[PDB]
Amino acid sequence: EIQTPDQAEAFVAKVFDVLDSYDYTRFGEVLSTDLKYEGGLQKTSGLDNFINDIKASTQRMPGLQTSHSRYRTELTAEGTIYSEGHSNASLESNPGKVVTVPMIGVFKLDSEDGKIKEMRIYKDRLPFLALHQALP
Amino acid sequence: EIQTPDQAEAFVAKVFDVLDSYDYTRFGEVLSTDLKYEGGLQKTSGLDNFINDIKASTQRMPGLQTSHSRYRTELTAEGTIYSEGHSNASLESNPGKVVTVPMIGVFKLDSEDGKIKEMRIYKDRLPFLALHQ
């Protein structure tokens, strides 16, 4: 399982590689079915409701592309992952305009399979109004 | 110094009682002069630059009132304070129309006087556009 901050950061990179692929069939590899997610005022319980919300947002922002990087991750004695990095988005119809904001993810893992059971993402969404006006 | 999460929480509560007063002469009580601050796209180095950025931001939302709560604070072996809570904002002209968003603070302390030398605030500022109406 996850025992060091470098293992924690590698898992977070893997998690966002999956999320940013929008391959929804692979979300269950790293996210618990009972995932408790909070992203600002967006809040869901259950992996199905998480996927629905992402899908509802991909319909409102056609051509949306996202990527993530991280540079500083701590794994605490309580098992909490704090991972600071950046969130990037652009529209395929205008690939030159990229919006980037700092972001931090707070994660709790399932004690059996090591999937994310709690995921709280903090970032400022106001800059993304430069892409599309139908944000989460 | 800071040794328990309870002490970390109380310091963060004191820090935002100073920040939410907007008494810029008191900021230097809890913020180091070399403060490295990041709040979304806003990024400042030095306490004077931080005060100027907060001044500029408040000057365009006259009547702004802010407060902060917290429910989950961790103090790590590295001395990092992660504090999850909420950020509230309203206008003095309509004090019952409040916008509240979740917010997390990342803090690092000066080992000599205990003031904040690194403060990185993460929240969504988009909902606060509702205050302009």
Image (cartoon, coloured by chain):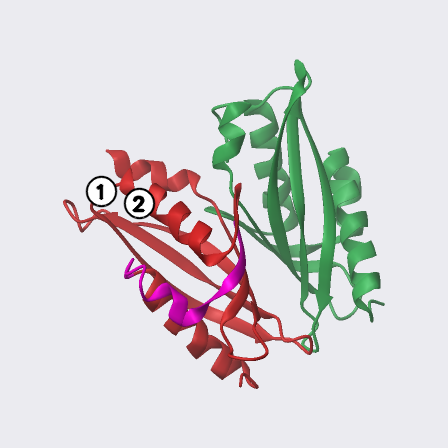
Chain colours: A green, B red
Instruction: Return the chain for callout 2.
Output: B
B25 inside magenta stretch: yes
Q: Quadrant of residue B108?
A: bottom right
Q: Decide which of B97, A5 is in the foreground and name it.
A: A5
Query: x, y percentage for residue B24?
Result: 32, 59
In three-dimensional space, the C-alpha distance between marks 1 and 2, rounded to whole angstroms, equals 6 Å
Circles 1 and 2 in contact, beta carbons < 8 Å: yes
The region drawn magenta spans B21-38
Q: Provide the residue designation for mark 1.
A: B62
Q: Provide the residue designation for mark 2.
A: B58
The residue drawn where x is 52% and y is 24% is A130
Q: Decide which of A68, B39 is in the foreground and name it.
A: B39
Residue B98 in sight in this render = no
Number of the label disc, if any, that sits on residue B100: none
Query: x, y percentage for residue B95?
Result: 18, 51
B6 inside magenta stretch: no
